[PDB]
Image (cartoon, coloured by chain):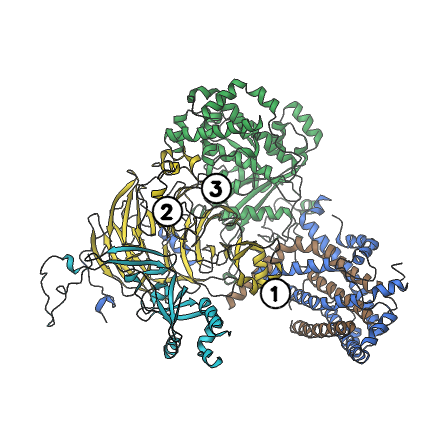
Amino acid sequence: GISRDSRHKRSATGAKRAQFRKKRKFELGRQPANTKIGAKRIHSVRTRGGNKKYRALRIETGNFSWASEGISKKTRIAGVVYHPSNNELVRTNTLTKAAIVQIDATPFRQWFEAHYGQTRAASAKIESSVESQFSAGRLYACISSRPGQSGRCDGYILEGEELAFYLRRL
Amino acid sequence: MSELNALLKDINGSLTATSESLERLSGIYSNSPAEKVSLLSLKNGSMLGYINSLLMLIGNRLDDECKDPSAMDARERSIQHRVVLERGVKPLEKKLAYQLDKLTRAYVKMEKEYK
Amino acid sequence: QSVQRDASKGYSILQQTKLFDNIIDLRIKLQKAVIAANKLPLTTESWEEAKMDDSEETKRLLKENEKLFNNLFNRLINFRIKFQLGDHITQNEEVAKHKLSKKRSLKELYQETNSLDSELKEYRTAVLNKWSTKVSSASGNAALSNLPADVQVENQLSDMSRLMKRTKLNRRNITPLYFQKDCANGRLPELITENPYVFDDEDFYRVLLNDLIDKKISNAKASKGRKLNYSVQDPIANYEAPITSGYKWSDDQIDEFFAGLLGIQIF
Amino acid sequence: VSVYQVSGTNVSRSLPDWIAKKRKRQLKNDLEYQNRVELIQDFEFSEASNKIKVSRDGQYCMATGTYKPQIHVYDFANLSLKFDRHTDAENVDFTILSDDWTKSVHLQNDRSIQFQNKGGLHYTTRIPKFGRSLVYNKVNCDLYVGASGNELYRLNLEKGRFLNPFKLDTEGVNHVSINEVNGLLAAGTETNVVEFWDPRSRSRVSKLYLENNIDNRPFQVTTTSFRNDGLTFACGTSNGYSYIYDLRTSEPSIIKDQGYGFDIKKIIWLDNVGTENKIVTCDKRIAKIWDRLDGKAYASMEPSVDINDIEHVPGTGMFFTANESIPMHTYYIPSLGPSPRWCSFLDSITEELEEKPVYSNYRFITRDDVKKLNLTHLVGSRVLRAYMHGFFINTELYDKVSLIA
Amino acid sequence: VSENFLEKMMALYVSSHYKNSPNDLQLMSDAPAHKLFVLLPPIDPKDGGRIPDPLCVIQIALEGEISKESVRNSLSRGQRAGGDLIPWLISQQFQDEEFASLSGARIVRIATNPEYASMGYGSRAIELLRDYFEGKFTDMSEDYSIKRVSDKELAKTNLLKDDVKLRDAKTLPPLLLKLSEQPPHYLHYLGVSYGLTQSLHKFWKNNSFVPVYLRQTANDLTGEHTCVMLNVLEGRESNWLVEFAKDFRKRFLSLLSYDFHKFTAVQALSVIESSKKAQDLSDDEKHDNKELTRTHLDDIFSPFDLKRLDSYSNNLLDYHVIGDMIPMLALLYFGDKMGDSVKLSSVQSAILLAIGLQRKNIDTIAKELNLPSNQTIAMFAKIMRKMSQYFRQLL
């Protein structure tokens, strides 16, 4: 039923074009994948060609990357906090790309103690806000993957002016 | 720091707290023609006697000389007020509880309407 | 007028609860003092043995302890005198005002406690017998004619010895300072677990706290359709038909309930 | 009281269902597979269900799914899937206008309302702002749709036109419900208030401020329902507390705690079945049946997966619970009433049912709350009993302690 | 004013009754045992004392305190004295002398505004009325007799000059009295006499009354059976009610076949529950139901009968083969001899009661309960299976 054909729209002049032809299979769309936090739950989608797309209907874990330190760890996703496109995705805790989520900081905390031996010092120094978040127990991260296409919720921890701007918006 | 020093200090602060709360208690009473219920009033008058007996027992406990250490006089008075609350006043309140609650319920409703 | 009288009594009843609840708060604060008091040294020698540990510091605290206690036990008597006066418990207005005006020593204050107790003792006999009569007649016990409260109070009071032993019970297992030393030296004649010198009113204390806690609980732009368009829509026109019978309740009854929603001498 | 689960997932909570299908080909040999019994064939969405309701006839059951967003319409007479129709988005709510399955209204998650006849989608209309609930007043032929905005939008199917919206003091409408005998349209806003509206007139009959003495955390109403008698009323708070208000007086008759701190997703007034004084409260994890007058729990139905919505087949013991799992669970409480007509021989086979059996009785407290309440000293005492990451306590003791704090 | 109020009372009073007679007015006015109670809405202070319409009116008749010698002497003569209905009936049916000596008040009539029926006002009035006699409405603030015409005044008045006037208002007491002002009479029980209907029985069952008697002969005018229901106030002896409630329960179970076969299965069941609630009122364990003994079982049922029972549970028999045993099984279960081991749902209890005691055919139950015959038999077999298992356990 969903279609991407541009024939139905009005012409640039504003004329109402007539229905040229029936809907074709090569111009289809599929229903959105409202990823919500919960037990992992994905089903494959057989797309054009032999390719396959994974639909992340539900997901609770993701690989998140600390870019400044250039490390990546698998962490649980606590909950959505702020989403730029629409707010009501925040209310229902829906996951999509560019959504800001709160992730458990425990693996990063353990790794940091392992690598730096601190709860040498100048390198260990990190932004004040990130240390405050570590104290809190949850880290603000931005999802970089597209859960409705690849079935993953990979992303990275907010840092610097990213963190400043999003904290202001919060 | 001697064990007695800790006890004196613990008594010292506890007594000081007793002073502030009593001063607040006196002020609230002074703020409070509305007719005061006799039985419930006696309950308060009875209990203030009980607290008075407790303090005068403590005073005997504070006294270094300790002439009457078992503190029969303070202990007897504490019994006197205790029995009145437990055995005399308390059964009457339960038998009067329903009408007391109803009367109080009437006021809070009216005060809401005025507000 | 009658509603106003009921309201005023309802008002008056409340402060008695609030005033009582405050007195509970007074007892709660004093609970630490009573526990510390029972632990204190029991004899002059133990008190002397206690003082030597920190002579200067103990001397300072003992002086401070005397002052605040005397100021307190002064203050309680003043409030008690005022309370018994305002509630008409004491009828001699002039004497009460004189007592408030004059400062009192410890012995004089001890004397006043006896006078206040005696005034209360007479008041209890009148009030308890008064209310016992009211309740029994209300219950029909007068029509029936369970002992009167004033008589009940005396019977328990006559049984002082059992009340004597209940307090001596050391439920808390409090051990006074240098208690073992005084026992070894035969300085504690009464003893020569129930300890006469230790006072335990925790059972009464626990009942009061339970009563306080329970009372609290009982009291407790147009694009995308973002602008509304009221123009008729043919596909949904006449999608369904109304029921002519109407709501189950009559229109009158419905109106009355909505109005009330969420709130000769005849009388 | 005995509770029998007729249809549902039988695996443990930790082990997810899709593995069960993978194991199932390995478990074809086991006698349990041959002996396992399901009433309605294909009584399952691909990944999960959202909302399930039974038609007035009692002949048809309707549901909505996660992916692809589908609308199954089960026929009881044939114990089968009569038809499944796809949609363009997920469903937040729907109501079956006609007595049968024939005619229905769906509020999707894209601010759209869809009208579906037998053949298929009939017409689509889009309300000005996002919708959250839906109700139909049959007498006036008006469709009332809750909205994230202050306006409570009103749509008239008979005249086929939006009429003037009802303005509400606060912005947000989580649920709407209509008193059948009266017609009061109780709107449950995000703040602790329910705005009761006369439908015939356009007025605010009153507003009811909910109060929770135990907790100071602000809470949101999530569900409202009226009893068929017409005078009693219900509410569900975001803190997990359900209330029963008698409309004539503002004070709450009872404040029962489910205890898990999870919102109250639906409330069903079990008047018809028998022993009318029973009310069902549903949470994310547990649903409990308790008497409306005394507050004593009767029986509780705990599935091993989150409950999205529950519904009661009228005049029977069957309980349909829409879950977040592939099968849609069915519950039969024999004590309440007889089994439905279409499950004639369900009674005979009662023994082979699982007969699933503390947890519904007590309240659940997390570790953090224990520190907040300074109940740490009781850790390890008989007062507090453990299960997953929190301890259980008696509801009265919790209310005793929380007030103290 | 009193005339205006009197009419409003009679309007509410007469409205409930099908065909009232004028004589009851005299009974209300003259009879010393009768007192009138009125439930009034909240009075607005702004009304200036305007009489509010009565929402519920209760007429109670005080009864009891009969001398034991009078009870024994008149019972031997079989003569009923005028008044004191409930004491006389209960004494006759139970042959107990103690109850007649007890004091009670009978609720002769209760009426509520028909438009406001079912709104819960009826349950409020009884609740307040019950609390009144228990003694809860005690006065909180620290006479109503009228001076009678003296013989001297009567002697000094001449027939021609006699000035017949309404009594002066100052002498008269107030028309409506707060409950606190006038003390209640000491009472042991409150009683009701009414024709058995489902709406009424539910109303009284909710108000903590207990059934003690049911008249076998249906009333000719109404077709209903008169029932006597009693309640014991707090702080009074309760054993006698418990003994009556049990014994009446035993009468009902056997009597269901003779004349109460017309009663619906649900209605008959509810009466049992109300009586059983009386047992719950007795916290004492002195009077408790006895579990059936092994010897008692053998007397009732032979070994072949038990084997016949078990085979049906295994579905190796036809239903007709166990038709003979259903009534005895019904008596044992509803008598509570079987104990906590066997419990049944509301529907199953209704089914067993019908075949067992009503002696109704299986198809008749299917229609009354709106179930198919197949399910009714299937549910019944489950009841038997529970019963067979218990006998196995006891053996």
Q: Which residue is mark 3?
A: E14
B105 left or right of D349 in image: right
Q: Give the answer, above or below, for where A85 lies relative to E42.
A: below
Counting other residues with Cα less than 10 Å from the Cα at mark 2, is it few (<14), some (14-19), or many (20 or more)? some
Contact check, label 1 and label 2, Cβ < 8 Å: no
Q: Give the answer, above or below, for where E383 lies relative to D331.
A: above
**Circle number at residue C11:** 1
Q: Position of residue E288 (x, y in %)?
A: 63, 33
Helix, strand or loop at disc 2?
helix
In front of the other: E116 or E361: E361
Measured in 3D between alpha carbons, the distance from the residue under mark 1 to the one under mark 2, in whole angstroms, is 67 Å
Q: Give the answer, above or below, for where E390 lies relative to C153.
A: above
Which chain did the image draw in cyan? A
In front of the other: E123 or E361: E361
Which chain did the image draw in blue? C
Q: Is residue E244 visible?
A: yes
At label 1, which amino acid type do we have? Tyr
At label 3, which amino acid type do we have? Val
Residue B102 occupies which quadrant of the picture? bottom right
At label 2, which amino acid type do we have? Ala
Q: Which residue is mark 2?
A: D20
Instruction: Tell me the shade of chain D.
Output: yellow
In front of the other: C94 or E16: C94
